[PDB]
Length: 233
Length: 232
Ligand SMILES: [Zn+2]
Ligand SMILES: [Zn+2]
Image (cartoon, rainbow over all chains, first blue to last red):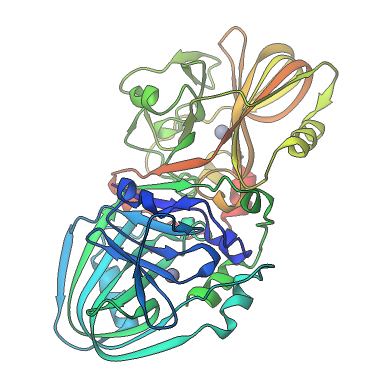
């Protein structure tokens, strides 16, 4: 019952985009997860043991041995709660509904939503070149995609506020379409005909990078929570 | 290479003093650690695989099966950096020196200081009766112990700021005297003739309690950082 957390969101804010975590190791830690890749070269998403790199060119590439990440989160997803949604529901209404059925706001959850969405809006981070800029700068020109009447899967994690800055507190969701070509990090969505599954997690295992970039990063950011809202909302 | 973290400091602040973590399980998770016991019935300290409950009655009781904790931290201590301190050094001077030799402020460390202390000041949290008050209120009358010219051991953890509220950011140290009777959570100390050892840790595993008390706790506390300074 664990979320395996690779590095911290505050390190990613500081422009630490080169990690040492080998994505070839994913099956040791989960069959489900999200994150990004070294150099912010695309969005990571996976479930049922199949992971993808989604880039702003509208392609999904399989995760391949040699791929590395500075920030990602995994779990072995088990469906502890299931809920059907058969009528239009906005993101706000959805968070309210899910929050109402969780056993506690103080635990970690993995969430999956499969089905038809009236709308999903995503962004996809793009490959950065050294010298790296802070992520609030990096995302300023991030590509934003609007999908209508789209079928696919949203996966992610629900993180309690005490963990903000390690992970993203609240709902952190990525999307991939039924065709497995397009999607990214989710900003907004409207559900139409979906099955929601939730997996409750009682442990969070944080793995720090053994890199000079992490060791030497200045992670004192008094405004980290606002910066996380800017980059992830 | 992990710190095993049982529950959060923010839940302790909120009066979640009854945990479900069985202290008999310690050997799975470390040979070294600090924290407290259910009901805040004493301070937990251990190293070299030997753990104690230090109570405000000036006794130390070995940990037994059936002992439970709402908050504690463990690791298998591996010396990575060892230094002799052979002259008087205040707490402030010590922290400055240790901070200057750490490879990164972004990692977790375990720390041990053994030897002769000119002074140590500790507190020992005391058993609370339900319904539980917040920790800032529960430590208002906390028992304080003062030690002078004492041999013993300080152990604990240095925690990066990004983990504050899960654990105590900065230095969190507990003490036990050579006689194994007395000590507690450290507020101040002056070294005299000591050896310091540090163990670097790259992983932190947070284990949450399976209790209604934790599940139902209101852990929104905008002022948690100040409250941790107050209690610790
Ligand atoms: Zn994301
Ligand atoms: Zn303490």
